[PDB]
Length: 128
Ligand SMILES: Cc1cc2nc3c(=O)[nH]c(=O)nc-3n(C[C@H](O)[C@H](O)[C@H](O)COP(=O)(O)O)c2cc1C
Image (cartoon, rainbow, N blue to C red; front, side, top):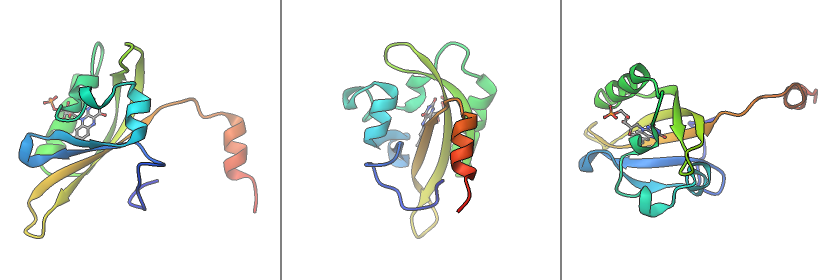
């Protein structure tokens, strides 16, 4: 669920400033809760700091290329919370362009992968 109303009180995202080398300019409350990092470790930084051992170099290259090309993208990447816990991050990226069509910012929406249970599916599919 995206390309739909987005606020911090519900969602996990960050916003990068393309005019400052894609440094994060804003992070939702969910982002801090998910990663365990606080603003002092995030604002002004690049989100690559979440990557670590075993993060897939070819998925990282696909992200880098999508951003350079100004394209939307998603891919699952291994990331690490502040305590060193690995987690799978389903990262969706979307450019933000000005009226001249230049990329000025990127939004990144992260979803920490959790197991989806037969019970949760029953709830999703449960009629009417
Ligand atoms: C808005 C935005 C959000 C991002 N969020 C994450 C993230 O949650 N985890 C991550 O590993 N990389 C994230 N990235 C990707 C890195 O910032 C970086 O673009 C990627 O590692 C590829 O560039 P590099 O090869 O220079 O590291 C995000 C990028 C952007 C632009």
